[PDB]
Amino acid sequence: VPMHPFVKALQEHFTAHQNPEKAEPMARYMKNHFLFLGIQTPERRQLLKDIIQLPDQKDFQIIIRELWDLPEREFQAAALDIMQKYKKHINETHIPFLEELIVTKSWWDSVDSIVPTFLGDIFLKHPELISAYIPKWIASDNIWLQRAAILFQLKYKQKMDEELLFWIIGQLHSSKEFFIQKAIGWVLREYAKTNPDVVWEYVQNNELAPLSKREAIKHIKQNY
DNA sequence: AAGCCACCC
DNA sequence: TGGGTGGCT
């Protein structure tokens, strides 16, 4: 049971609008790792908007963690919507907090929402901190921290640290894990929108799982 | 906005 | 494999 009145209110309001018919397919979509109330994103954001109609910033970590601790997945999704509203107050001191979120109730929906936006932004401002985290994440054998190392630069475009990206990928290219092979393909394909020659040269000269290579070049292969 | 693509199998 | 699909940059 949540301490914070905001979370108590969100819990009651979400629960009052649950849809058991939708909960089953939503749960199986996520391989039944989580219970669902059965509330999709548009309705979930409207219900959150209801309750906000914003807690002090000193409460934001308390609120997020309380939501993270609740069983139904919509509360973690709502927690990430809430964290967006505190964007300007999130900085390098929050990396360990974000790490905890990544490795707790982990799946692609939370991790892909946390990493290219919040960690991406932090490391753009503090690139001198990357070596304190990225190698650690790679060495952790936690696939979500590994996916975090791969994807924190996903949205960088011209800001991409190419040599860092390629080093991270080389460290993880031998992973058997689908979510790692796919993340490698994804980030290379995305970066190829900005710097296609360099992604082509990388893929032609460095070992990748076939899934990763195929995904990387599927929109530039017709140019070479 | 919506063009793109995570996920699913 | 690539269509179905819901949501993000």
Image (cartoon, coloured by chain):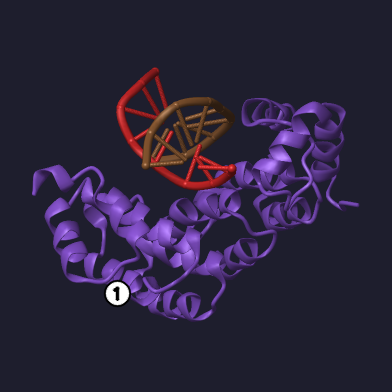
Chain colours: A purple, B red, C brown
Q: Residue at x 38, y 68 (%)?
A: A126
Residue tagged 1: A167
Residue located 62% across and 26% down the image: A42
Rendered image quadrant of residue A193: top left
- Percent across and percent down for residue A20 are 83, 30
- At 25% from the left and 65% from the top, the residue drawn is A161
**Placement of A80 over or under A208, stated as above or below:** above
Residue A211 in view: yes
Residue A77 position, x and y percent, is 65, 44
Q: How many marks?
A: 1
Q: Decide: is A178 above or below A134.
A: above
Which amino acid type is shown beneath numbered disc 1? Answer: Trp
Counting from the top left corner in percent of width and height, residue A175 is at 44, 72
Q: Report the chain holding disc 1.
A: A
The residue positioned farthest toward the right in the image shown = A1
| Residue A1 place in picture, x, y as percent | 91, 52
Give the left or right position of residue A115, taking residue A8 as reference. left
